Length: 50
RNA sequence: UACCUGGUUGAUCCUGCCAGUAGCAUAUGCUUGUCUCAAAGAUUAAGCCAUGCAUGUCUAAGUACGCACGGCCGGUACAGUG
Image (cartoon, rainbow, N blue to C red; front, side):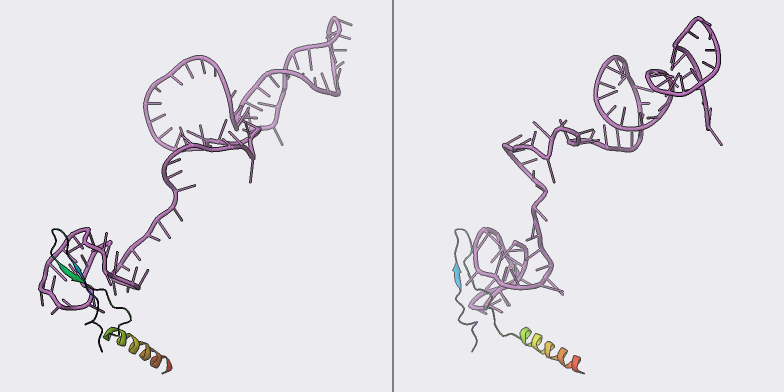
């Protein structure tokens, strides 16, 4: 299950400022970039063996 | 530029040093218009030190929920600057 729909967002409201919400960047989140990095590492291993 | 000169005697020839002579380094005195370089708290005390400064550092690429700013949509995980 994804965790992006449970990140605690803090509401921001300041005197004279438009209100908004803030969420942190989720660490150790498996993302396509992470899998691509893992696959590139595996491909480098393949290339070295060959 | 491989150079000497005065001084021992009544006079002479010597040994011989003293004193002259030129540079170079520090100091000092007097004087000083232009211009280019340029040493400089070593010598005595590696003595003692008020104060300020002399060592900091971020890229697309470690960690950004500081509205501290801030949007080409804001249920956006993380826009961006930081």
